[PDB]
Amino acid sequence: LAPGSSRVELFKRQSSKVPFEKDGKVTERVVHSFRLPALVNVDGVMVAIADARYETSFDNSLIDTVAKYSVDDGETWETQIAIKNSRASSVSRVVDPTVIVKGNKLYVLVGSYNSSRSYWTSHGDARDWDILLAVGEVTKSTAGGKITASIKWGSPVSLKEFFPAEMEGMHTNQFLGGAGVAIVASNGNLVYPVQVTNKKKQVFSKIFYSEDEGKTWKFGKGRSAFGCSEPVALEWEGKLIINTRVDYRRRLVYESSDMGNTWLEAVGTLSRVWGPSPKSNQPGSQSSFTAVTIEGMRVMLFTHPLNFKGRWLRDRLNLWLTDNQRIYNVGQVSIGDENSAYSSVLYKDDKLYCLHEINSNEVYSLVFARLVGELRIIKSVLQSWKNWDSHLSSICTPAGCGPAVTTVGLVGFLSHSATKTEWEDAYRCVNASTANAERVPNGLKFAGVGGGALWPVSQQGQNQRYHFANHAFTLVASVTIHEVPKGASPLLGASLDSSGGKKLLGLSYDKRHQWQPIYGSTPVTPTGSWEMGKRYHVVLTMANKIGSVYIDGEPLEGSGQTVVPDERTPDISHFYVGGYKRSGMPTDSRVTVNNVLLYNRQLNAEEIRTLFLSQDLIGTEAH
């Protein structure tokens, strides 16, 4: 939890009480565990919705959906049960409450089970299942000169009638919301990303939406891959972005521009960025994933535990900030090494909050945190992004001005800022490590075996912000060679392995004053010519499994070559710059590199030309 931030235990395990209604009687009952936080703003009233697991944290036990609401930004709260289970048995439960806010209404979708003690994904059929929608209506009043609010919960309605018996190649079994908070699309539709099972017990995500305020529901035709559960979605630039949990694998993120009719993996932005554990081989988690506008910039906030412990412990809830280009680790929201899996982040009236689980010995509370430090950090980073984008965009490029330098898809930029061991990302997300580097205006001058900079890709580890590079990228830099090498020496490239010996696409230079563009494993053909001391503009582009290298805005011989065998998807380890940064690699690159730009797409010809013409103008040095 960042400095300045603070929290309270709001839904306190084995302590907080809820109004338990049964057989027409209501008793204030202590709840063992609270899980599945959903925190929203309904017309000025903060509402925290969750599972009240009365007797045990075990999923298949007695659970009602609890709501707490506050009209003073979380200082004080009222408590209610928003949805009660069927009371059919000792383990009846309404589960995975998923919340949409629209106007003054809360739409809450829950699965409902009567007696099963088994996990829902293990059920061979739906005999124990129903899917219910309850609507809470929030009204504010000022009887008494002080703001008050109340929420009237309607009886739940089954939406089972809207669940088709079959979907393409399958027979449906059950579905649930993805938990947390869902959305109202810009066209007014209520949109729930849902997790669905078929009779083979596979799980997959779908979009389940309503065009008539929840009276009828439809499923989008398309779906995620199997294995994607607890989906969470937001709308971004006219598309749904569906961010899914994949146990034991990296999280898959999809985009859909037609209400779920078609799903495309967001390989160029957010898919596979977030791993569920350091080695991405443990269970995943529910995640808060929202689009908000902070100081005029639309961005997305995403949370997920880092889970260093493994299994479902899911310690170290981390918050991420992204404008769909750069992905910034705001930091750890939870405290120390506590288990802290599920969460919900709310941005309301320029304050940031998070309601999240803490788990000791399988007894769970929800803490309500005021993310003061986090918002401060976020605003600082966004200012940096807006400022560098503005700086680059405002440059009058050489003819009257030429086309603007493009910042669309610009993800990282290594320029003037650098410390003894790092070359700093102007966008503040991923620095490059360096060796044998001397600072020069807008870059670094390298020399000696082991010299160079390493801009990590898979080397980022659990969370891989540059994963998009495995699908498409453009890497741009200005370079100057100061010494003729003994053989061929590296200047710039994307490496598939840690050494730099296995390259996806790179540029080297040789003793015959020729460039050696390297296209994957293709035998290298030296080409062109360069002179010592002259600065050259280098662009490496990769898209559709094809690599190109440009020098001074012109593509080198060999460009347009396949760099990825059509079968697999690359796993780039890092970009190397100005050397391999590997003492074990035999080369000595004596070169200066300035202004390294990384884009998450293949730049077009005009864009490349503009960057070439504007090389002397883009540095961060004076700014």
Image (cartoon, helix red, strand yellow):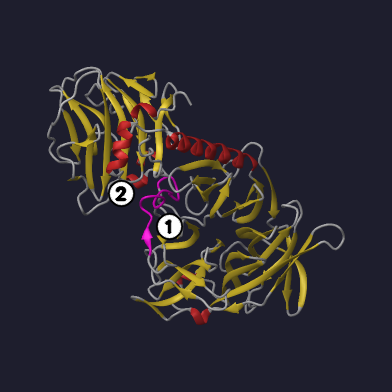
306 horizontally vs 530: left or right: right
Residue located farthest toward the right when viewing the structure as drawn: 144
Q: Nearer the viewer, residue 314 or 259?
A: 259
Query: Tags 2 and 1 in contact by the CB under 8 Å rule?
Result: no
Q: Nearer the viewer, residue 142 or 334?
A: 142
Tag 1: residue type? Asp
**Secondary structure mainly formed by the magenta segment:** loop
The quarter of the picture where the N terminus appears is top right
Where residue 156 appears, x then y in whole percent? 63, 77
Where residue 85 appears, x then y in whole percent? 63, 74
Whether the magenta-drawn stretch holds residue 205 is answered as no
Q: Which residue is mark 2?
A: 471
Whether the magenta-drawn stretch holds residue 268 is answered as yes
- Spatial CA span between label 2 and label 1: 23 Å
The image shows residue 232, relative to residue 570, as above or below, that is: below
Q: Which residue is mark 1?
A: 247
The image shows residue 500, relative to residue 419, as above or below, that is: below
Magenta stretch, residue numbers? 263-279
Where residue 610 appears, x then y in whole percent? 32, 36
